[PDB]
Length: 111
Length: 5
Image 1 (cartoon, helix red, strand yellow):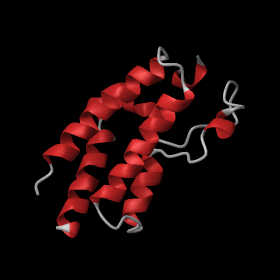
Image 2 (cartoon, one colour):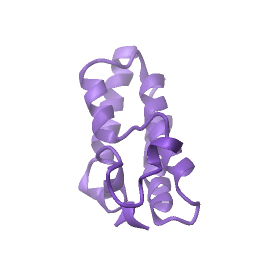
Image 3 (tube, one colour):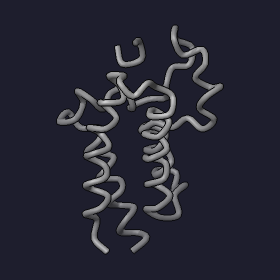
Image 4 (cartoon, chains in turn brown, blue):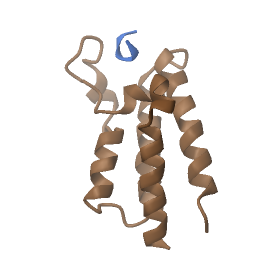
């Protein structure tokens, strides 16, 4: 189970990285660039940054004990975006579309 | 705003 579910988790992240979703997924591919103009306060507000490449790397290094831990990191990524940005920000609408994908796949995972 | 280009 633990084993089968984490393989499903890898599949979910793979879909999140797919061309199908790239139009709204791309801001989450790599760590937020805290050096860029506009993001000088990012680390004041976000104590635990997370992004898809870091999650992919965590899966591959077997750093998740179960699907729950994988799921917590994906949701951390989304919550960081909701926390940092104004709710009318374009990146927030992108996060929701990507989260729709994750939540639906994560929920439909066999048990 | 910039991060979403």
